[PDB]
Amino acid sequence: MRLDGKTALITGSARGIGRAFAEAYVREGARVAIADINLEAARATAAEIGPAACAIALDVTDQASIDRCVAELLDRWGSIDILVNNAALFDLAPIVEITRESYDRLFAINVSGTLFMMQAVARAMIAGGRGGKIINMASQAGRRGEALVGVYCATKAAVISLTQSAGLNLIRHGINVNAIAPGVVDGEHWDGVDAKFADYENLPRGEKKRQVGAAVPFGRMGRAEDLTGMAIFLATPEADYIVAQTYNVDGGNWMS
Amino acid sequence: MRLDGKTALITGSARGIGRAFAEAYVREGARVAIADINLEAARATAAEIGPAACAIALDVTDQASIDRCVAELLDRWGSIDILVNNAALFDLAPIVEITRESYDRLFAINVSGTLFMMQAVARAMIAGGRGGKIINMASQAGRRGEALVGVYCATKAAVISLTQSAGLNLIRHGINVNAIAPGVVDGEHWDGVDAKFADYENLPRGEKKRQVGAAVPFGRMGRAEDLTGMAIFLATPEADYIVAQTYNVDGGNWMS
Image 1: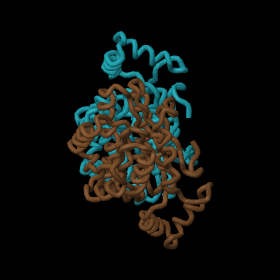
Image 2 (image 1 turned 30 degrees about the horizontal axis):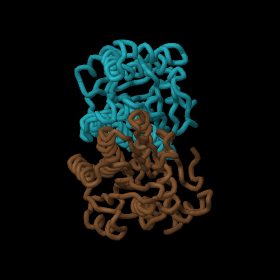
Image 3 (image 1 turned 45 degrees about the vertical axis):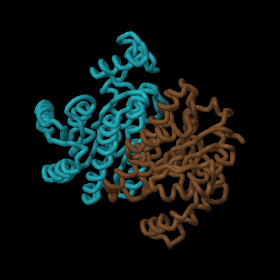
Image 4 (image 1 turned 180 degrees about the horizontal axis):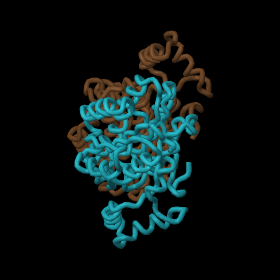
């Protein structure tokens, strides 16, 4: 019970890593909110997790949806103790092929979504008068640029920047802001991603995903379970002195 | 004449640092384009600099304006050898006071403008078949976040990221992409900026501009003349092996 009697809002937690954190958080005695743009999947996951989880519709790109979300949880819980900006989108393409739609969309969700979601919750925490914890999800992509991932990389670099700015600015109110930077995490999305690289680099279908996983010092592609420990640690008082940091949990993929 | 017989498009060069680069490039024997959103000012500076400089209206936030600018210059010069993305906006405010309006502009001009402007000129350079030089303008603000400069810092962090992604992707076509990161450059704009900080941190009017200047290791605030040397160098062949780098020219304000 490392998170006993605490409330956590996790964005884009209907599936993937977001769901993992939710399950882990609940296991530690915390009440979580499965926020997602599709209320169907949200309710499904929330019901699958138990009485400790509840669903709620959220479009991080829409201010109205953001203010509704926060106000509703405030009445159901009385206070939001932890916020995990997990909602994000991925895409890839060389410089000369980047489209305005790719740019517009990734920045709207990855950057804009994280920022205003932070602002909404931070304003509540300040009012609450008892601080809180905010964890952003960066990525190794945000540490260094890549030839075919310009747009995605740039959004993650921005997240790291915002974590530092928010961190220094909000710590005075007792709010810790830090981020976690995963490396290469397995998931179904790798089917198409691999196809993309295979086509962009003249590589056999499936070679890319193989190369990537073998290049990880640890010796394998990431897993959600590799991240939950840190997700929990940063939310405990044993981390009260950790401010505006981005911790890499990537099996050695990148060293910071 | 280190840039003899070359052409350079410099965005937002009607005034400030952008104008200093243009005057310097013209001194090294190059033909330049004073691109600005205000053609009145653009023409004025072009006439002031001489027969080597021409004016042209450009709004880096509008694809149409971007394509027209490149096409026109291609007819006038035949090729664009150098592109300096200098156009940018500055703004500051605590997290809880950041407006969508502030976010929208800065990202539109500082990030979006740099990316698509890069793509347009890169396309031309690749078609040209003889490569080229691209120089982005970063900032110390892109190296680490600040409490009251969240938006601006995030945009510059994204620039550094885009400079790396483009650098790695375009070097294969003979195009060098790098960035310059100035520290605190003196300006009139500092009049209002100082007022802002003075009001935000309970400081005497003018104390902020003083403190910042005194904190620079070198012993004084930046000047446009401090940056021209690096601007020229990165466009010469002595920098052909320099790829995807961001060089700080800040008198020691930040170390990389």
